[PDB]
Figure 1 (tube, rainbow over the protein chains, first blue to last red):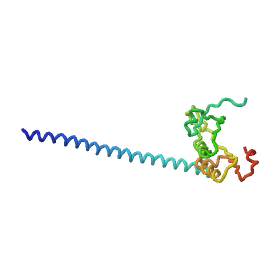
Figure 2 (cartoon, helix red, strand yellow):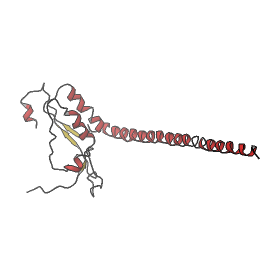
Figure 3 (cartoon, rainbow over the protein chains, first blue to last red):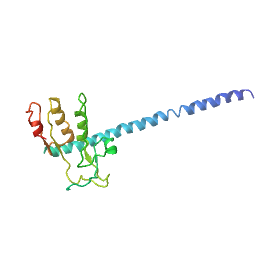
Length: 62
Length: 114
């Protein structure tokens, strides 16, 4: 019938839009994990540096 | 007669040298500097990033102690301290011999000291 056409113009948009917004809610969240990981990768190198420098200084000093 | 061609290169921490000229042991390489130009800045970079290759050349010389010698021939108030504080960056002040000549020091010792 004619009401069955109407349910199909909607039922198409409301999956196109909600599939799109579940891949932005994916995407932001993927970059959020890859940032936190990298802000701790730079933190890891820094600490190392400070320890290699530190020990050399105490060897020279002594 | 007592020398022979060297061939063991070092990391100066400046790309440009270690490609184009290749700074090896027993070789000079003046760094020409103008007047109204820095001289101090650039020098410091070569002192804290001077290091042999571990086997990147096919060998090292890290197996024998690497050390540095200094001797300044006329220096002011800033150049005095500027050098000393980058030698603590270097971590070398227990294995270096410094022959600092100032400008408040005699002018005759500017050619003796070398």
